[PDB]
Image 1 (cartoon, rainbow, N blue to C red):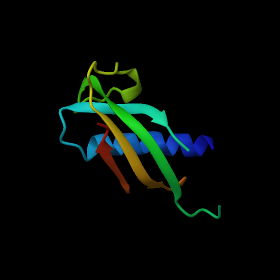
Image 2 (cartoon, helix red, strand yellow):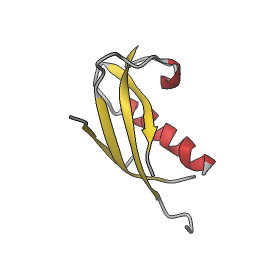
Image 3 (cartoon, helix red, strand yellow):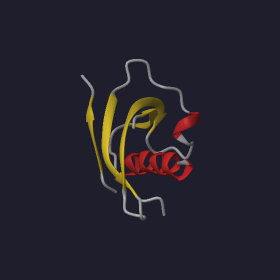
Image 4 (tube, rainbow, N blue to C red):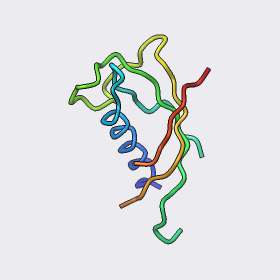
Amino acid sequence: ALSYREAVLRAVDRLNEQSSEANLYRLLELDQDPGTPKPVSFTVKETVXPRPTRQPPELXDFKENGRVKQXVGTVTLDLDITXNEVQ
């Protein structure tokens, strides 16, 4: 369960790697067993930090009128998420 949340956080970081959007996204909301990958659903929201920034997303304020994405797929507790913009 702590591994879970932490892996979601790592997925947000990787999304920020594979991105070419201008700004870092950060976790907005986290929605709802042998070792097999675990299903994740969460949202992310755009921040005021430009994308090439070694500051963790969580130190970056959310951007007013920042795009929101709903992300779904899996994580291993030890990439395969697609995000689509919320309307």
